Image (tube, rainbow, N blue to C red):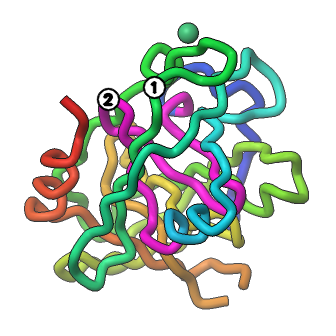
Amino acid sequence: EKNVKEITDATKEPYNSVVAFVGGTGVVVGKNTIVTNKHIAKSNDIFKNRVSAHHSSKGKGGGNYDVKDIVEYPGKEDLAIVHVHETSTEGLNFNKNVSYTKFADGAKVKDRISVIGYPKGAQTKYKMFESTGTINHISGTFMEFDAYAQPGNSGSPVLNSKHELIGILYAGSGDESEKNFGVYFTPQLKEFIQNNIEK
Ligand SMILES: [Cl-]
């Protein structure tokens, strides 16, 4: 599918759970805690950029936040937890400015999904886009889906029709792409993520 739309104002759910990194996307699941790709977290640790809470073209800014620590998923899956320091250098509270997206606990082939992130973020001044498609394949912690994606979509949450989190985009076939790959969250991955949410 190639069906995309700018989210001009990302202050409402679930858009206010999406975060921009300098080169990718993530999603907020709990206190100070973002899920993204392992590769996005790692690249961001070279340049040590802050995370921008739900950056969009219009609407009140949610703050930029310093990265506190990273927990990489031990296995092969391109998955990592990024923790942020809660208070920005302007006094904004990370938690007051995002939502915590709940888990879908799986999906089925043929389900209609959305991928929300920052395709070509550096060139667009980090406009948020939602792109719609379908899940075409699921196997263990892998899924394939046909929502249009571009570089900058890494780490993008893949949401079901009730805005619940199925997994995150990590790679494609292109770059630039209509056959994309995600990390699909099984119970074991949901457990790793939930054990790494700040208390
Ligand atoms: Cl605040």
Q: Residue at x 63, y 68 (%)?
A: 46
Q: Is residue 20 left or right of residue 14?
A: right
Q: Is 14 part of what is drawn in magenta? A: no
Q: Residue at x 36, y 40 (%)?
A: 33
* CB under 8 Å between discs 2 and 1: yes
- Image-quadrant location for residue 44: bottom right
Crowdedness of circle 1 by 10 Å Cα count: few (<14), some, many (20+)?
Answer: some
Q: Residue at x 43, y 20 (%)?
A: 95
Q: Is 25 part of what is drawn in magenta? A: yes
Residue 115: x and y, percent?
53, 55
Residue 137: x and y, percent?
32, 80
- Image-quadrant location for residue 74: bottom left
Q: Report which residue position mark 1 lands on.
A: 86
Residue 48: x and y, percent?
63, 56
Q: Earlier in the sequence, mark 2 or mark 1?
A: 2
| Furthest-bottom residue in this view | 173
**Disc 2 residue type (three-letter):** Lys
Main SS type for the magenta part? strand
What span is colored magenta in the figure?
15-39
Looking at the image, residue 44 lies above or below residue 69? below
Looking at the image, residue 12 lies above or below residue 124? above
Does the image show residue 41?
yes
Residue 148: x and y, percent?
64, 68
Does the image show residue 1?
no
Q: Report which residue position mark 2 lands on.
A: 31
Residue in the foreground of this view, choosing between 153 and 180: 153
The quadrant of the picture occupied by the N terminus is bottom right
**Disc 1 residue type (three-letter):** Glu
